[PDB]
Amino acid sequence: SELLVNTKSGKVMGTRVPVLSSHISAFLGIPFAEPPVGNMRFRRPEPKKPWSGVWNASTYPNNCQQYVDEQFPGFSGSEMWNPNREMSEDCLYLNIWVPSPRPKSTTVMVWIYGGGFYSGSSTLDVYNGKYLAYTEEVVLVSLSYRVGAFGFLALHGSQEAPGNVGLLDQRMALQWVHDNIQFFGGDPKTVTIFGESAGGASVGMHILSPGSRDLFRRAILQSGSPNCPWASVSVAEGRRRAVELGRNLNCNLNSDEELIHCLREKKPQELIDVEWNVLPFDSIFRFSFVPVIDGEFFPTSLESMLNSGNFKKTQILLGVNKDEGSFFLLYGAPGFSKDSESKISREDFMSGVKLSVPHANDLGLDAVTLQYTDWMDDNNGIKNRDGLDDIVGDHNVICPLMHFVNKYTKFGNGTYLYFFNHRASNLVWPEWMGVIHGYEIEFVFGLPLVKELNYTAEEEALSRRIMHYWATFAKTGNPNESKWPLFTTKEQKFIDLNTEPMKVHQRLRVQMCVFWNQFLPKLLNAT
Amino acid sequence: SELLVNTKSGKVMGTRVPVLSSHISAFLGIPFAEPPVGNMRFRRPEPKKPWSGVWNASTYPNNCQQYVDEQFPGFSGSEMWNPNREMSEDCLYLNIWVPSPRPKSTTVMVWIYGGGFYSGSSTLDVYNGKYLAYTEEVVLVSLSYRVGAFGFLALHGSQEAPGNVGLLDQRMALQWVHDNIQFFGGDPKTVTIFGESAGGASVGMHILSPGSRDLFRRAILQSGSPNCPWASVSVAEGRRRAVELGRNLNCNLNSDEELIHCLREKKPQELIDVEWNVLPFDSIFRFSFVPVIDGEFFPTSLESMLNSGNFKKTQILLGVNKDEGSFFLLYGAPGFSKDSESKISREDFMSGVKLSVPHANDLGLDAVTLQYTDWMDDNNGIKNRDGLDDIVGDHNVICPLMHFVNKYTKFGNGTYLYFFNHRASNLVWPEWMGVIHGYEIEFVFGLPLVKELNYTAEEEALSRRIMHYWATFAKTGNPNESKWPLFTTKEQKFIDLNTEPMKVHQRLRVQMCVFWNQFLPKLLNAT
Ligand SMILES: *[C@]([C])(=O)O[C][C][N+]([C])([C])[C]
Ligand SMILES: *[C@]([C])(=O)O[C][C][N+]([C])([C])[C]
């Protein structure tokens, strides 16, 4: 049967889902690891002991324990990102959408969800891979990984909580995809892993980590790169926060064993409740438990790896949205509110920059302010708001990504860069927030095709183009069958991705990125 | 006789000069100090022992010994600034142009010439005060002062070469004007001292130095302020350069006395020949012998004086030209030539910034470059040239002046600010040089009125407006009888001064000046 599939783990029974006046198969909730519960919490993922009998993959799996957002209870704009299933430590499962008739060998697209590494669900509605599968004839897999303490608590040195385990959960699902995707119609020699934010960052880490490079062919990174400042921590830092979390739970802190054991008796939500109390700064766009540069998953500093070509050479397609920071200002900067134009006074501006660049000394915060301030109109609220928006985004997404793209390209085999700048017509977030972080996702997965969603004709157009660019890149290493230029260090071309006739530009935010990538760090090192 | 005048020093016999189809009196070469020759070299000025008999002031006096510019022999554009009279250590003389009929009590305008303190002549043709005298009915005095080692060599502590003696020569002429200008038709209670560059800097120093404040009423500062980085040196620095000059002349350097004595046997040109060998840096816009912050002429650091209101409160009219730096790049930066468009490569750009900000460490030169570079078009030669032009000017003239104007205004009684941006139609300097340093002078003195000079009708217009603004400011403390706004720290208004209908703007180069006046020094202090 088109829904019964055999895999090296056991048989799996999917279900067929209807899609745009048609249908496809969906094998949802196939497990790829032993449930990381009990004494296995914090431990590296374990392969799923095979099973016998048909595994019933007719419905979405639980979501990993995580911080649920209640900032705007009921507001769809934010709840659309909250776990829509029971959360459980038993969440390591993958979902596959397969065109019907089942292909014999098509390109595979594996989606790694975002969420600052503290959250994420492969079950969100915007991550519904059927329109892409259907529309582009690709096998869409979306995996899940442990987030939060559960996936990133790092007591480097113990094997009980080595850290990066949430990155190994992804590898592991990449492995299950390598080994079994052939029985679903997918070609394991043509899987493109793609992700947004912590997911696009994950993608780039699999591109760097030796033990993952072989499990996929191409990569698409959306609004994130392995080198984003919020993407990783030193082992010492990860240890500090690990201990600190212990303190907030009154754990014996005399040893990693007593520590890990205490943290394992704790119910999930107890860890979640104090999760944010461990950051070392009053900051915006920093999450507590993130990958640690351990010397195992990552051999040395991501930067020396970037510098020495020590990474998987292949083709990559990446980009950023216009207003990446708005979302984080709205949530943790004073002066911003969901319901006002959030015009910002210098007093609140000056506070926003301090939160955005937590590690800067005063001369540093002075350099940022000098660069992002219109001294000829310094008390404009609109300008202070937008200026703060560019600081949060340039510093945390746009510039670290530009650094990666320029370093990778030196050794890669084809880089394609976009700048997404389209505000969905039906966005329920305030206009001041612009083209928000995470809002390209819905175009990439084809929601603009389902009319009951109220997108506009041209937006439908744009979706289809984006799904084609993405699918067509997955299959061939090139987005084009109107050419989206190849990005080269010399010319630096990239393209806009909005409902207008595309246009090519060069040097995405150079002025600013020279500041953040070259000047600032030099400044902060001198002082 | 209209040409015979009595003064407390002796009688003086002028001559009448023809002016625009009319005439006026001119008393040229009246001495105000004992000739600073022989053992008096480097010494403070001595009052002119009175004389008996008519002193014959019918012709211009010698010019002070100084470095003559031979960079472009015969090129008028540069020779127009060279001494046009025999140079001599006997040069302390003043010149007075008086309307005919001799007024009983008109406003007095005393011109202090510029020249980096290393040069200057009160006899240049552009400093010809008859059109202003005639046209505006003001008594125009133009004084002279010792420049170079002769006027600024400072061996602080000896009374034989105290330094600042060239500033005392000016004071002294201000004194002779105070005491005698009444016998020429001038009102000694309404003298406006005005100067350009080292002269506008001098003006502001008389505004600060306690012993000069009383000798004048109002001040006009053109392209210079007391706080310009090239305008003064510490006593230690002045001593260093004093000694160093001695080294270049093989003077016994065992003591100030042996040193001063050696320097006094030296013929004038021997001091001039090695004058430039003493700067402590490879730099552009730095001169060797300049006023020293001695604790006598200047009580404390010009900056604490600026900060504490310790200065003459009155009305001041000041401003800068659009392209102040071009002239110094042309002469000491590689890549610039008088006969080419001087497009500049980054390699030469990067060398120009090093020369422009000699005291900056690397992080400093990195901050300047980041600010003055168009990263989206970094290999443009036009942009690198102009960018270097703005660096030289912003750093050396425009921003220190903006600092003074903002500090003074806090305690002053009326500040008027202009931005001169008109390139004379008949300028013989390359277009790339723009509105050059020193090129407002000719409009201020009314040369555009003499038709045999080929200026355009609208330029004639502009001259007359400028002479009126200047004269009308001198007489009343206000440029207006189309209003030139008063500059306030709050609004910061200023006006353009060109042949188009004037316009008011605010915040002259704020972006940049916050960089130079606030950020840079903070940066260079941290590192
Ligand atoms: C990145 C940092 O993982 O952020 C994702 C943001 N979100 C779409 C609002 C959840
Ligand atoms: C200032 C520094 O005194 O410069 C005057 C420049 N000049 C008009 C070219 C002689």
Image: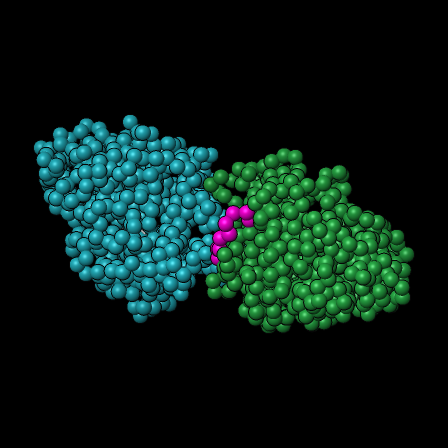
Chain colours: A cyan, B green
Q: Is residue A18 above or below residue B1?
A: above
Q: Residue B144: x percent and y percent?
A: 77, 58
Q: In which quarter of the image is the C terminus of chain B?
A: bottom right
* Residue depicted at x 16% and y 53%: A85
As for residue A7 lying within the magenta part, the answer is: no
Q: In which quarter of the image is residue A492?
A: top left
Horizontal placement of B408 versus A394: left or right? Answer: right
Horizontal placement of B161 versus A172: left or right? Answer: right
Q: Can residue B485 be seen in this view?
A: yes
* Residue depicted at x 69% and y 57%: B133
Q: Nearer the viewer, residue A69 or B363?
A: B363
Q: Residue A104: x percent and y percent?
A: 19, 28
Horizontal placement of A46 versus A20: left or right? Answer: right
Q: In which quarter of the image is residue A491?
A: top left
* Residue depicted at x 65% and y 55%: B135
Q: Nearer the viewer, residue A185 or B506?
A: B506
Q: In which quarter of the image is residue A369?
A: bottom left
Q: In which quarter of the image is the N terminus of chain B?
A: bottom right
Q: Nearer the viewer, residue B227 or A485?
A: B227
The residue segment tinted magenta is B498-507
Q: Is residue B196 visible?
A: no
Query: In terms of secondary structure, what is the magenta stretch mainly?
Result: loop
Q: Residue A444: x percent and y percent?
A: 24, 40
* Residue depicted at x 47% and y 62%: B491
| Number of numbered discs visible in the structure rendering | 0
Q: Residue A130: x percent and y percent?
A: 17, 39
Q: Which of B490 and B371 is in front in this view?
A: B490
